Image 1 (cartoon, rainbow, N blue to C red):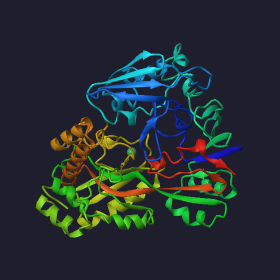
Image 2 (cartoon, helix red, strand yellow; image 1 turned 60 degrees about the vertical axis):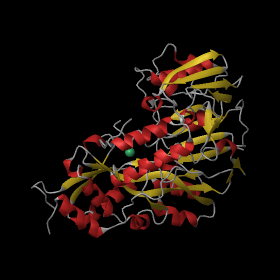
Image 3 (cartoon, rainbow, N blue to C red; image 1 turned 90 degrees about the vertical axis):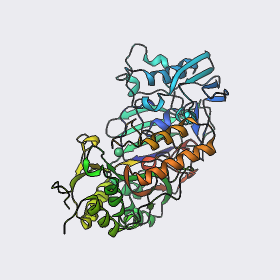
Image 4 (cartoon, rainbow, N blue to C red; image 1 turned 30 degrees about the vertical axis):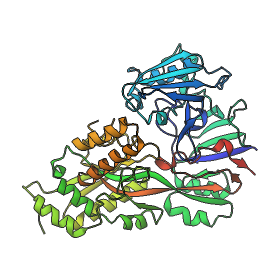
Length: 479
Ligand SMILES: [Cl-]
């Protein structure tokens, strides 16, 4: 069934499941021991069975025999051991290493049976082991960081790599020997189009099939007779990072005040135009969300009635230091700078002078900024975007440190009983409400314009910028 074209707004860096955390073309070329299903639950993929011991420290996998890479080489436990051990390799220096560092060792006791040993109990291990397995033989004479594999990948996904034109497109075609049952499309081309206006016209002409839409352009793509617009809930949220290195935020009442000075629903209508929801929780869409924590209910008078007791007064000053900072917000996510523009201008009504800076990611250092507009949230396990974000620390960049939040996130990370994992995640959220690390804003809605000739799309809670909207493209149908 011919070709399906995707107009991606970001271009891949390396086509290796390790070294990269982005859910770009890697999601169509590689698969792992597990794979998230329709309900964002990791189900066996490359492995056919697994069982855990009574301490929960040993994950006894058993692999499907005959799994072939793109080069028609059989996948064995060597490659699974190679992929997971190369993450923890100190010299490879992967970005995902702190996310797998609770693994003691990954053992191969059989060509088709892998054993994963942890340091301590880690229930969300199967969530992380959905990482793609790479062939070990393609790396012997190379060093894995600068290997040619990152230019021509070989994996076990339903679409093998074909061609990559830098700055233009990545070419894949249907892998006939793929183990999963598949739809009818035979070619998948990912066009890198950063300007959302070109994506709209390429959807209008039909030059592309799918495109992540900004909220402002949905009203026109709606009128298109050849495009359907998908509006689906995500776990992606934006916020403001309270850099704890700044004494302006060491008083918690100042942060609670700044949280009180935001019209988040007015932000849902101003910037999102209703395609979103006010943010108050680090795990709002997660099943372990605490519905009754202290949300900061747009209390303009409480913000102005917290700074003066905290010491800040004019009409802006405490001890002569004048209450002003700089809010950093990167470009190519123009919702964020519009949020920052709205953030600073709405903090003017409480006597704060903020300088908003729209900069490029290659010039921003988050841990050096007074306040940064972050973009986090994940629809998988509650440990994904919480431990590495609200701990002494992963890459917690706001220097946040709460002793009860540290323990609450560690118990839920280490305890098996999910009903009590709810308990610890509920106490962490409650403590995060009174001791805020972030100034939460809005939760986002993924907007995709899909051509009317495409079938098979199944919605679910998505990740960053719609990461995982095309999770089942190998079952989508042309005509
Ligand atoms: Cl970010």
